[PDB]
Amino acid sequence: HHHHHMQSRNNNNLKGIDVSNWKGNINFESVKNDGVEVVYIKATEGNYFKDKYAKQNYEGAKEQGLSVGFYHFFRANKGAKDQANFFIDYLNEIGAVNYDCKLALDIETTEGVGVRDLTSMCIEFLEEVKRLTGKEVVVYTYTSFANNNLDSRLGNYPVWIAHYGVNTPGANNIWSSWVGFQYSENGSVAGVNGGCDMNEFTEEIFIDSSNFNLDNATTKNVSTKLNIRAKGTTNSKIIGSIPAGETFKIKWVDEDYLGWYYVEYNGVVGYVNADYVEKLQMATTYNVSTFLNVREEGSLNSRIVDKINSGDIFRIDWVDSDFIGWYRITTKNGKVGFVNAEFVKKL
């Protein structure tokens, strides 16, 4: 019968780990060369504990070009906003002003607090952190803990779920999807002594969400279809095709194959001859201090269907003649609509 679950692990996800003072000295270059891409570091616990290795780990991780995040171990017996401030004050105290991942609330104990109140406290903490940093947050906890000692109100925040021994986090009555999955506490990672905490993170773990990762190219001078080959060579095997006029995503240009684009179209990843590729027009906001409305059609009385956050990247699809002065676009979230030209900067 029906069994709704969260997504399973996926090699396509970012490889991550999380450390604390318990690990002592860590060789981050080694961690960097072990495939690890993001590192969450413990910063504080309650309003009475500072992880003394946070600065060392933050600087070490950043030196290796790794993405960094910090987590606070919540102690419900202490003030919620008090702890939020304790947490942020310490990050500043150690000069950690360039973390790349959402601030994490590690909630895994109740300290004897009821469900309604414990959930309320977590919310207070989360909002205070957002208020203080203007940055986003993520909730870390274990499946059964959430199902028994917290209520669904925390479902408004993304979750970094912990559940070992499985390829899929278990049934959850608060979240239906995760941005982080801690699947093991006994992993073996170069540069970390003993058993290391292992994680898979989706791109939503990042604070910077301005990127556009949808199709950015289409064909040109192609009468019917554009061949996708295993390598940038007609001597290479055709592993796919792109019908004329369709869009796809250019990943990058490979050195061994200049003059070709490494792309992805409907599941296939290969090389295409650049002479037949036309890049689509990317753009961002201009003179937008907050956000830009995306409307159903190019008019001020038209239903607002989405928003473009200052600095976000979107695609200009075409100019609809019915709405001169506006662009028909596609947002980083796949949504289509119109935006006022006075606020767009082509890239």
Image (cartoon, rainbow, N blue to C red):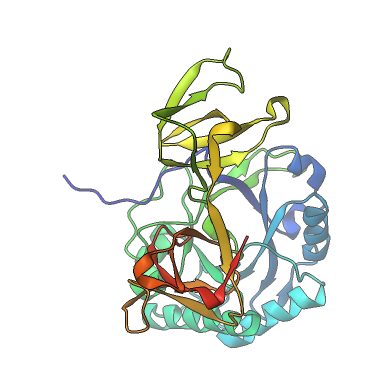
Comparing 15 with 333, the one in front is 333
Nearer to us in this view, 236 or 91? 236
Q: Is residue 278 above or below residue 48?
A: above
Indicate left or right for 234 with 36 as reference. Answer: left
Residue 123 picture location, percent across and down:
47, 80
294, 183: nearer the viewer: 294
Look at 64% across and 84% down and name the residue there. 132
Residue 311 placement (x, y as % from top left): 60, 70
Residue depicted at 44% across the width and 72% down the height:
326
Question: Relative to 75, is 334 above or below?
Answer: above
Vertical placement of residue 296 versus 212, above or below: below
Quarter of the image where one finds residue 339: bottom left
Query: Is residue 95 in view from this perspective?
Result: yes
Q: Position of residue 317 (x, y in %)?
A: 45, 57
Tell which residue pokes out farthest to the top in this image: 235
* Residue at point 46%, 74% (across, down): 325
Tell how many labels.
Answer: 0
Location of residue 52 with respect to 240 vertically, above or below: below
* In this rendering, position of residue 209 left or right of residue 68: left
Whether residue 76 is visible here, answered yes or no, is no
Where the C terminus falls, by quadrant? bottom right
Q: Is residue 331 left or right of residue 3?
A: right
| Foreground of the two, 196 or 68 | 68
For the N terminus, give its image quadrant. Answer: top left
Residue 292 placement (x, y as % from top left):
49, 77
Tell me what residue is drawn at x 82 percent, y 72 percent. Answer: 95
**Residue at the extreme left:** 1
In which quarter of the view is residue 296 placed? bottom left
